[PDB]
Image (cartoon, rainbow, N blue to C red; front, side, top):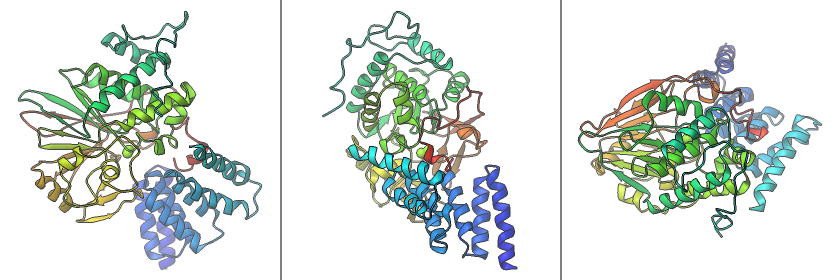
Length: 467
Ligand SMILES: [Mg+2]
Ligand SMILES: [Mg+2]
Protein backbone atom coordinates (compact mmCIF):
# COMPACT_ATOMS: atom_id res chain seq x y z
CA UNK A 1 0.00 0.00 0.00
CA UNK A 2 1.31 3.40 -1.12
CA UNK A 3 -0.98 4.97 1.48
CA UNK A 4 0.01 2.31 4.06
CA UNK A 5 3.72 2.75 3.26
CA UNK A 6 3.21 6.47 3.92
CA UNK A 7 1.53 5.76 7.28
CA UNK A 8 4.49 3.46 8.06
CA UNK A 9 6.80 6.45 7.46
CA UNK A 10 4.56 8.80 9.49
CA UNK A 11 4.66 6.49 12.52
CA UNK A 12 8.46 6.44 12.19
CA UNK A 13 8.50 10.26 12.00
CA UNK A 14 6.46 10.52 15.23
CA UNK A 15 9.04 8.25 16.93
CA UNK A 16 11.91 10.54 15.96
CA UNK A 17 9.80 13.54 16.96
CA UNK A 18 9.01 12.47 20.55
CA UNK A 19 12.76 11.91 21.14
CA UNK A 20 13.82 15.35 19.78
CA UNK A 21 15.36 14.03 16.53
CA UNK A 22 13.55 16.72 14.54
CA UNK A 23 15.80 16.57 11.46
CA UNK A 24 14.76 12.94 10.88
CA UNK A 25 11.14 13.61 11.85
CA UNK A 26 11.08 16.18 9.04
CA UNK A 27 12.67 13.75 6.56
CA UNK A 28 10.31 10.86 7.34
CA UNK A 29 7.33 13.23 7.25
CA UNK A 30 8.40 14.44 3.79
CA UNK A 31 8.79 10.80 2.64
CA UNK A 32 5.25 10.09 3.89
CA UNK A 33 3.93 13.29 2.29
CA UNK A 34 5.51 12.17 -1.00
CA UNK A 35 3.68 8.81 -0.96
CA UNK A 36 0.48 10.55 0.19
CA UNK A 37 0.46 14.35 -0.46
CA UNK A 38 -3.17 14.63 0.65
CA UNK A 39 -3.39 14.11 4.42
CA UNK A 40 -3.69 17.13 6.73
CA UNK A 41 -2.10 15.42 9.76
CA UNK A 42 1.13 14.78 7.83
CA UNK A 43 1.35 18.51 7.15
CA UNK A 44 0.38 19.35 10.75
CA UNK A 45 2.97 17.04 12.28
CA UNK A 46 5.73 18.34 10.00
CA UNK A 47 4.73 21.97 10.57
CA UNK A 48 5.38 21.41 14.29
CA UNK A 49 8.81 19.86 13.62
CA UNK A 50 9.63 22.83 11.36
CA UNK A 51 8.42 25.13 14.15
CA UNK A 52 10.70 23.44 16.68
CA UNK A 53 13.64 23.84 14.29
CA UNK A 54 12.86 27.57 13.84
CA UNK A 55 11.72 27.10 10.21
CA UNK A 56 8.72 29.43 10.52
CA UNK A 57 8.25 29.88 6.75
CA UNK A 58 7.98 26.16 6.02
CA UNK A 59 5.95 25.78 9.24
CA UNK A 60 3.45 28.35 7.94
CA UNK A 61 3.36 26.67 4.51
CA UNK A 62 2.61 23.21 5.89
CA UNK A 63 -0.04 24.44 8.33
CA UNK A 64 -1.81 26.23 5.46
CA UNK A 65 -1.83 22.97 3.45
CA UNK A 66 -3.27 21.11 6.45
CA UNK A 67 -6.08 23.66 6.94
CA UNK A 68 -7.02 23.65 3.25
CA UNK A 69 -7.10 19.84 3.20
CA UNK A 70 -9.23 19.88 6.37
CA UNK A 71 -11.06 23.03 7.53
CA UNK A 72 -11.90 21.18 10.80
CA UNK A 73 -8.32 20.11 11.72
CA UNK A 74 -7.88 22.21 14.88
CA UNK A 75 -4.14 21.54 15.26
CA UNK A 76 -3.74 23.17 11.83
CA UNK A 77 -4.92 26.52 13.23
CA UNK A 78 -2.85 26.09 16.38
CA UNK A 79 0.32 25.51 14.33
CA UNK A 80 -0.33 28.25 11.77
CA UNK A 81 -0.95 30.65 14.65
CA UNK A 82 2.21 29.36 16.36
CA UNK A 83 4.09 30.05 13.08
CA UNK A 84 2.73 33.58 12.67
CA UNK A 85 3.21 34.08 16.43
CA UNK A 86 6.83 32.93 15.99
CA UNK A 87 7.38 35.80 13.53
CA UNK A 88 5.36 37.99 15.92
CA UNK A 89 2.62 38.32 13.28
CA UNK A 90 -0.02 38.32 16.01
CA UNK A 91 -3.01 39.73 14.08
CA UNK A 92 -2.88 36.77 11.68
CA UNK A 93 -2.47 34.42 14.68
CA UNK A 94 -5.57 35.92 16.32
CA UNK A 95 -7.67 35.14 13.24
CA UNK A 96 -6.83 31.42 13.54
CA UNK A 97 -7.49 31.21 17.28
CA UNK A 98 -10.72 33.05 16.48
CA UNK A 99 -11.57 30.35 13.92
CA UNK A 100 -11.18 27.64 16.59
CA UNK A 101 -13.33 29.41 19.23
CA UNK A 102 -16.30 29.43 16.80
CA UNK A 103 -15.99 25.71 16.19
CA UNK A 104 -17.54 25.93 19.66
CA UNK A 105 -14.98 25.27 22.41
CA UNK A 106 -15.19 26.52 25.98
CA UNK A 107 -11.67 25.12 26.04
CA UNK A 108 -7.98 25.78 26.55
CA UNK A 109 -8.45 27.31 23.08
CA UNK A 110 -11.33 29.60 24.06
CA UNK A 111 -10.45 31.51 27.25
CA UNK A 112 -6.71 30.72 27.25
CA UNK A 113 -5.32 30.90 23.69
CA UNK A 114 -7.55 33.37 21.81
CA UNK A 115 -7.85 35.77 24.76
CA UNK A 116 -4.12 35.85 25.59
CA UNK A 117 -3.16 36.37 21.92
CA UNK A 118 -5.67 39.24 21.76
CA UNK A 119 -3.95 40.83 24.77
CA UNK A 120 -0.60 40.71 22.95
CA UNK A 121 -2.06 42.29 19.80
CA UNK A 122 -3.48 44.96 22.15
CA UNK A 123 -0.26 45.54 24.11
CA UNK A 124 1.57 45.77 20.78
CA UNK A 125 -0.95 48.39 19.60
CA UNK A 126 -0.06 51.01 22.26
CA UNK A 127 3.29 51.38 20.49
CA UNK A 128 12.32 60.96 22.21
CA UNK A 129 15.09 58.62 23.36
CA UNK A 130 14.80 56.61 26.59
CA UNK A 131 18.34 57.63 27.65
CA UNK A 132 16.69 60.95 28.66
CA UNK A 133 14.31 59.72 31.39
CA UNK A 134 17.31 58.45 33.38
CA UNK A 135 19.17 59.92 36.35
CA UNK A 136 22.44 58.40 37.56
CA UNK A 137 23.14 59.45 41.18
CA UNK A 138 19.38 59.80 41.77
CA UNK A 139 19.37 55.99 41.90
CA UNK A 140 20.74 54.74 45.21
CA UNK A 141 22.06 51.52 46.71
CA UNK A 142 20.88 49.95 49.96
CA UNK A 143 22.49 49.19 53.33
CA UNK A 144 21.72 45.51 52.79
CA UNK A 145 23.08 45.05 49.22
CA UNK A 146 26.21 42.87 49.44
CA UNK A 147 26.75 42.74 45.66
CA UNK A 148 29.16 44.01 42.97
CA UNK A 149 29.38 47.76 42.31
CA UNK A 150 31.35 49.88 39.82
CA UNK A 151 34.69 51.28 41.01
CA UNK A 152 34.23 55.06 40.58
CA UNK A 153 31.74 54.65 37.71
CA UNK A 154 33.88 52.17 35.72
CA UNK A 155 34.08 48.42 35.10
CA UNK A 156 37.09 46.52 36.51
CA UNK A 157 38.22 42.86 36.58
CA UNK A 158 37.35 42.64 40.29
CA UNK A 159 33.88 43.83 39.27
CA UNK A 160 33.56 41.26 36.47
CA UNK A 161 34.83 38.38 38.63
CA UNK A 162 32.34 39.40 41.32
CA UNK A 163 29.53 39.74 38.75
CA UNK A 164 29.90 36.13 37.56
CA UNK A 165 30.00 34.72 41.09
CA UNK A 166 26.95 36.83 41.96
CA UNK A 167 25.18 35.43 38.88
CA UNK A 168 26.48 31.89 39.55
CA UNK A 169 24.60 32.11 42.88
CA UNK A 170 21.45 33.42 41.10
CA UNK A 171 21.68 36.98 42.41
CA UNK A 172 20.78 40.28 40.74
CA UNK A 173 23.13 43.16 39.94
CA UNK A 174 21.86 46.48 41.32
CA UNK A 175 20.04 48.54 38.69
CA UNK A 176 22.14 51.73 38.91
CA UNK A 177 25.08 49.53 37.87
CA UNK A 178 22.97 47.93 35.10
CA UNK A 179 21.90 51.34 33.74
CA UNK A 180 25.52 52.53 34.04
CA UNK A 181 26.73 49.67 31.81
CA UNK A 182 24.03 50.29 29.18
CA UNK A 183 24.46 54.08 29.00
CA UNK A 184 28.21 53.68 28.41
CA UNK A 185 28.04 50.64 26.11
CA UNK A 186 25.59 52.57 23.88
CA UNK A 187 28.20 55.35 23.83
CA UNK A 188 30.95 52.93 22.70
CA UNK A 189 28.75 51.19 20.10
CA UNK A 190 27.21 54.25 18.42
CA UNK A 191 30.75 55.46 17.60
CA UNK A 192 31.60 52.25 15.68
CA UNK A 193 30.79 51.56 12.00
CA UNK A 194 28.35 48.94 10.69
CA UNK A 195 31.36 46.90 9.57
CA UNK A 196 34.07 46.47 12.23
CA UNK A 197 37.64 45.82 11.04
CA UNK A 198 40.29 44.25 13.26
CA UNK A 199 43.90 43.38 12.50
CA UNK A 200 45.28 40.18 14.00
CA UNK A 201 49.07 40.61 13.82
CA UNK A 202 51.59 37.79 13.20
CA UNK A 203 51.37 36.19 16.66
CA UNK A 204 47.84 37.16 17.83
CA UNK A 205 44.88 34.83 18.49
CA UNK A 206 41.12 35.41 18.79
CA UNK A 207 38.22 33.22 19.97
CA UNK A 208 35.05 33.45 17.87
CA UNK A 209 31.88 32.16 19.56
CA UNK A 210 28.41 31.67 18.07
CA UNK A 211 24.95 31.74 19.69
CA UNK A 212 24.73 31.59 23.49
CA UNK A 213 20.99 32.20 24.05
CA UNK A 214 21.12 32.98 27.76
CA UNK A 215 22.79 29.73 28.84
CA UNK A 216 24.91 31.62 31.38
CA UNK A 217 26.45 28.55 33.02
CA UNK A 218 27.75 27.44 29.62
CA UNK A 219 29.16 30.95 29.05
CA UNK A 220 31.19 30.42 32.24
CA UNK A 221 32.27 26.92 31.19
CA UNK A 222 33.65 28.58 28.03
CA UNK A 223 35.52 31.10 30.20
CA UNK A 224 36.63 28.34 32.62
CA UNK A 225 37.90 26.11 29.76
CA UNK A 226 39.31 28.79 27.44
CA UNK A 227 40.10 31.37 30.12
CA UNK A 228 38.66 34.82 30.78
CA UNK A 229 38.73 37.50 28.04
CA UNK A 230 41.44 40.19 27.83
CA UNK A 231 43.58 42.29 25.47
CA UNK A 232 45.75 39.15 25.18
CA UNK A 233 42.81 36.68 24.82
CA UNK A 234 40.16 38.52 22.74
CA UNK A 235 36.66 37.21 21.95
CA UNK A 236 33.99 37.75 19.31
CA UNK A 237 30.39 36.78 20.06
CA UNK A 238 28.34 36.48 16.91
CA UNK A 239 24.80 37.46 17.92
CA UNK A 240 22.01 35.64 19.79
CA UNK A 241 23.23 36.48 23.30
CA UNK A 242 19.67 36.35 24.66
CA UNK A 243 16.27 34.59 24.38
CA UNK A 244 15.37 30.89 24.72
CA UNK A 245 17.55 30.38 27.82
CA UNK A 246 16.34 31.79 31.15
CA UNK A 247 19.64 33.44 32.19
CA UNK A 248 19.72 35.96 29.32
CA UNK A 249 20.11 38.97 31.64
CA UNK A 250 23.08 37.22 33.24
CA UNK A 251 24.65 36.66 29.79
CA UNK A 252 24.05 40.08 28.17
CA UNK A 253 25.28 42.07 31.20
CA UNK A 254 28.54 40.09 31.47
CA UNK A 255 29.07 40.46 27.70
CA UNK A 256 28.37 44.20 28.07
CA UNK A 257 30.72 44.32 31.07
CA UNK A 258 33.74 42.94 29.18
CA UNK A 259 32.95 45.13 26.15
CA UNK A 260 33.30 48.35 28.19
CA UNK A 261 36.40 46.89 29.87
CA UNK A 262 38.11 45.90 26.60
CA UNK A 263 36.64 48.00 23.78
CA UNK A 264 39.24 46.86 21.20
CA UNK A 265 39.43 43.16 22.21
CA UNK A 266 35.80 42.17 22.93
CA UNK A 267 33.31 42.44 20.07
CA UNK A 268 29.57 41.99 19.89
CA UNK A 269 27.73 41.47 16.62
CA UNK A 270 23.98 41.86 16.34
CA UNK A 271 21.99 38.65 15.91
CA UNK A 272 18.35 38.23 14.92
CA UNK A 273 17.46 37.79 18.62
CA UNK A 274 18.91 41.22 19.44
CA UNK A 275 15.65 42.68 18.22
CA UNK A 276 12.32 43.78 19.78
CA UNK A 277 10.44 41.44 17.46
CA UNK A 278 12.20 38.33 18.85
CA UNK A 279 12.84 39.55 22.41
CA UNK A 280 9.12 40.09 23.07
CA UNK A 281 8.45 36.47 22.03
CA UNK A 282 11.31 34.27 23.29
CA UNK A 283 11.92 35.38 26.90
CA UNK A 284 14.27 38.36 27.03
CA UNK A 285 11.66 41.12 27.36
CA UNK A 286 9.87 39.12 30.05
CA UNK A 287 13.12 38.43 31.90
CA UNK A 288 14.19 42.09 31.89
CA UNK A 289 10.66 43.19 32.90
CA UNK A 290 10.63 40.57 35.69
CA UNK A 291 14.03 41.51 37.13
CA UNK A 292 14.11 45.22 36.28
CA UNK A 293 11.53 47.39 34.46
CA UNK A 294 10.10 48.10 31.01
CA UNK A 295 12.37 51.19 30.90
CA UNK A 296 15.48 49.02 31.38
CA UNK A 297 14.23 46.85 28.53
CA UNK A 298 13.64 49.82 26.21
CA UNK A 299 17.22 50.83 27.01
CA UNK A 300 18.32 47.28 26.06
CA UNK A 301 16.36 47.65 22.80
CA UNK A 302 18.13 50.95 22.02
CA UNK A 303 21.63 49.62 22.72
CA UNK A 304 21.05 46.55 20.51
CA UNK A 305 20.10 48.86 17.63
CA UNK A 306 23.68 50.19 17.72
CA UNK A 307 25.22 46.68 17.65
CA UNK A 308 27.48 46.24 14.60
CA UNK A 309 26.24 43.89 11.87
CA UNK A 310 29.49 42.32 10.63
CA UNK A 311 33.22 42.01 11.36
CA UNK A 312 36.10 41.75 8.83
CA UNK A 313 39.45 40.42 10.11
CA UNK A 314 42.54 41.30 8.01
CA UNK A 315 40.44 41.83 4.85
CA UNK A 316 40.32 38.02 4.53
CA UNK A 317 37.69 36.42 6.82
CA UNK A 318 34.26 38.09 7.19
CA UNK A 319 31.85 37.47 10.08
CA UNK A 320 28.09 37.90 10.51
CA UNK A 321 25.26 36.19 12.40
CA UNK A 322 23.09 35.14 9.45
CA UNK A 323 24.92 35.13 6.13
CA UNK A 324 25.09 36.57 2.63
CA UNK A 325 22.61 38.41 0.47
CA UNK A 326 19.44 38.35 -1.62
CA UNK A 327 21.16 40.34 -4.39
CA UNK A 328 24.51 39.88 -6.16
CA UNK A 329 27.23 42.53 -6.06
CA UNK A 330 27.22 43.20 -2.33
CA UNK A 331 30.67 44.24 -1.04
CA UNK A 332 32.24 45.03 2.33
CA UNK A 333 31.86 48.74 1.47
CA UNK A 334 28.09 48.23 1.09
CA UNK A 335 28.00 46.73 4.60
CA UNK A 336 29.97 49.64 6.13
CA UNK A 337 27.38 52.06 4.64
CA UNK A 338 24.27 50.40 6.20
CA UNK A 339 22.35 52.71 8.59
CA UNK A 340 22.01 50.09 11.32
CA UNK A 341 20.47 52.05 14.25
CA UNK A 342 16.92 50.61 14.12
CA UNK A 343 14.88 47.41 13.76
CA UNK A 344 15.80 45.38 10.67
CA UNK A 345 13.70 45.74 7.49
CA UNK A 346 11.42 42.92 6.24
CA UNK A 347 13.84 42.42 3.33
CA UNK A 348 17.34 43.76 2.66
CA UNK A 349 21.10 43.53 3.29
CA UNK A 350 20.53 44.38 6.98
CA UNK A 351 17.84 41.70 7.19
CA UNK A 352 20.13 39.22 5.37
CA UNK A 353 23.11 39.77 7.69
CA UNK A 354 20.90 38.72 10.62
CA UNK A 355 18.72 36.01 9.06
CA UNK A 356 19.93 34.27 5.87
CA UNK A 357 21.16 30.65 5.73
CA UNK A 358 23.51 28.66 3.49
CA UNK A 359 22.07 25.89 1.30
CA UNK A 360 23.90 23.08 -0.54
CA UNK A 361 22.54 23.73 -4.04
CA UNK A 362 23.46 26.73 -6.20
CA UNK A 363 21.42 29.95 -6.37
CA UNK A 364 18.79 31.36 -4.03
CA UNK A 365 15.51 30.29 -2.46
CA UNK A 366 13.15 32.00 -0.02
CA UNK A 367 14.35 31.12 3.49
CA UNK A 368 12.69 28.34 5.50
CA UNK A 369 12.43 30.79 8.42
CA UNK A 370 10.10 33.05 6.39
CA UNK A 371 12.61 35.92 6.26
CA UNK A 372 15.67 36.61 4.07
CA UNK A 373 17.06 33.87 1.80
CA UNK A 374 18.93 30.63 1.48
CA UNK A 375 22.10 31.13 -0.58
CA UNK A 376 24.19 28.56 -2.51
CA UNK A 377 27.94 27.90 -3.03
CA UNK A 378 27.92 29.99 -6.23
CA UNK A 379 26.55 33.03 -4.34
CA UNK A 380 29.17 32.55 -1.60
CA UNK A 381 32.01 32.24 -4.13
CA UNK A 382 30.87 35.23 -6.21
CA UNK A 383 30.70 37.38 -3.05
CA UNK A 384 33.93 36.15 -1.41
CA UNK A 385 35.99 36.41 -4.61
CA UNK A 386 34.57 39.89 -5.35
CA UNK A 387 36.08 40.99 -2.01
CA UNK A 388 39.24 38.81 -2.24
CA UNK A 389 38.14 37.08 0.98
CA UNK A 390 39.00 33.50 1.99
CA UNK A 391 35.87 32.41 3.92
CA UNK A 392 33.08 33.69 6.20
CA UNK A 393 32.16 32.58 9.71
CA UNK A 394 28.53 32.58 10.86
CA UNK A 395 26.29 30.98 13.48
CA UNK A 396 22.47 31.14 13.55
CA UNK A 397 21.95 27.38 12.96
CA UNK A 398 22.24 24.71 15.66
CA UNK A 399 24.76 21.94 14.91
CA UNK A 400 24.96 18.55 16.66
CA UNK A 401 28.78 18.83 16.70
CA UNK A 402 28.71 22.54 17.62
CA UNK A 403 29.98 23.57 14.18
CA UNK A 404 29.94 22.79 10.47
CA UNK A 405 32.04 23.54 7.40
CA UNK A 406 30.32 23.94 4.03
CA UNK A 407 30.26 25.38 0.50
CA UNK A 408 33.59 23.58 0.07
CA UNK A 409 34.90 25.19 3.25
CA UNK A 410 33.92 28.72 2.12
CA UNK A 411 31.11 29.01 4.70
CA UNK A 412 31.72 28.00 8.32
CA UNK A 413 29.09 27.77 11.06
CA UNK A 414 29.86 27.86 14.81
CA UNK A 415 27.36 27.37 17.64
CA UNK A 416 28.18 27.90 21.33
CA UNK A 417 25.00 26.68 23.10
CA UNK A 418 25.32 23.01 24.16
CA UNK A 419 22.26 20.91 25.01
CA UNK A 420 20.31 23.71 23.32
CA UNK A 421 17.14 24.53 25.32
CA UNK A 422 18.11 21.66 27.65
CA UNK A 423 16.83 19.23 24.96
CA UNK A 424 18.67 19.01 21.59
CA UNK A 425 21.60 17.04 23.06
CA UNK A 426 24.01 18.96 20.84
CA UNK A 427 27.64 19.70 21.55
CA UNK A 428 28.82 23.30 21.30
CA UNK A 429 31.96 24.79 19.77
CA UNK A 430 34.20 27.85 19.69
CA UNK A 431 36.89 28.74 17.17
CA UNK A 432 40.57 29.65 17.54
CA UNK A 433 41.84 31.87 14.71
CA UNK A 434 45.36 33.28 14.41
CA UNK A 435 47.18 36.06 12.52
CA UNK A 436 49.85 33.83 10.97
CA UNK A 437 47.21 31.23 10.10
CA UNK A 438 43.77 32.70 9.30
CA UNK A 439 42.10 29.31 9.68
CA UNK A 440 39.67 27.76 12.17
CA UNK A 441 40.52 25.39 15.04
CA UNK A 442 37.27 24.03 16.47
CA UNK A 443 37.08 23.24 20.18
CA UNK A 444 33.94 21.41 21.22
CA UNK A 445 32.47 21.42 24.72
CA UNK A 446 29.53 19.77 26.49
CA UNK A 447 26.77 21.33 28.61
CA UNK A 448 27.20 22.06 32.32
CA UNK A 449 24.57 21.78 35.10
CA UNK A 450 22.53 24.88 35.96
CA UNK A 451 19.79 25.77 38.50
CA UNK A 452 16.31 24.26 38.01
CA UNK A 453 14.86 26.78 35.53
CA UNK A 454 13.02 25.85 32.33
CA UNK A 455 14.18 27.62 29.17
CA UNK A 456 11.71 30.35 28.12
CA UNK A 457 10.31 30.66 31.67
CA UNK A 458 9.88 34.41 31.04
CA UNK A 459 8.25 34.04 27.59
CA UNK A 460 4.52 34.00 26.84
CA UNK A 461 2.56 30.78 27.40
CA UNK A 462 1.51 30.70 23.72
CA UNK A 463 4.81 29.66 22.07
CA UNK A 464 5.18 26.65 24.39
CA UNK A 465 3.79 24.16 21.84
CA UNK A 466 6.61 25.37 19.56
CA UNK A 467 9.34 24.27 22.00
MG1 LIG B 1 19.66 33.03 15.34
MG1 LIG C 1 19.98 31.40 16.56
